[PDB]
Image (spheres, helix red, strand yellow):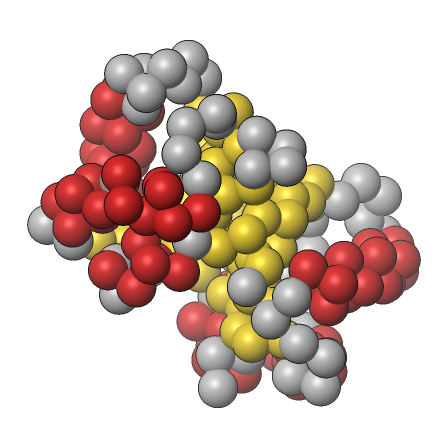
Length: 96
Length: 97
């Protein structure tokens, strides 16, 4: 299983205002191939936002990453800091 | 809830070898204050490793981050790339399913 972790500068709405504006966005992710779960990341004080995605395979993740970067440009996000890793299942199992 | 997102350079064991080797370390983490869960991340190809932790709050997260960054020096991890974020609970649930 691959874990996609990315964040970017963001001035946009935070907290509940963000949950409202980006609700359609969130729902569209559940329709992405190989998508397992995402934890939405945000930081008002540092003007950043992002997310931790978990895909079944690296190919599903890279595909999403490429697409979502293009998409993020419409929110005016010019640079996307991302990292794609493999998940060590045995250890992750121990930690919940 | 706070989310600690971190990773660093790494040559150490990977795959099952890492699972075997670091197993002690994993269960000692379930004992950390404010700790909820962790996803161990690794990339042998790029020689990197790290983890995604979810604590009950900033204080818990930062205290662990200070503790961990120090002991990581023993495995020869000079510097660590970290980020502390707040989680948007509503949206996360739409995608936690």
